[PDB]
Amino acid sequence: MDTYKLILNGKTLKGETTTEAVDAATAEKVFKQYANEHGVDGEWTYDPETKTFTVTE
Image (cartoon, rainbow, N blue to C red; front, side):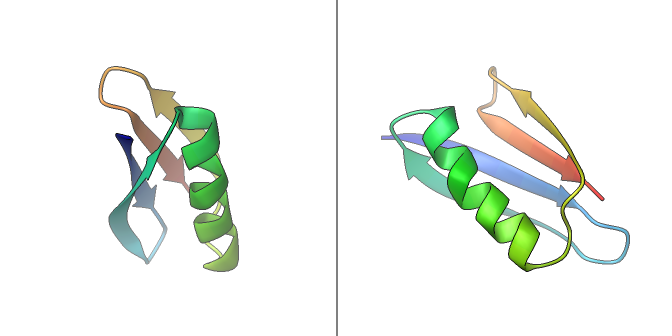
């Protein structure tokens, strides 16, 4: 399965993680779970070229 990346641009907490999934929509569920539970949710952007989501708090 394709690999999707998550870049977390938090005010204090910053990092990156990945998940493998059938498509970006499916991967995004994991990433939303992650950002929400870690209190670093914010504005989302998706880049199809790099299969990367960025969330900026």
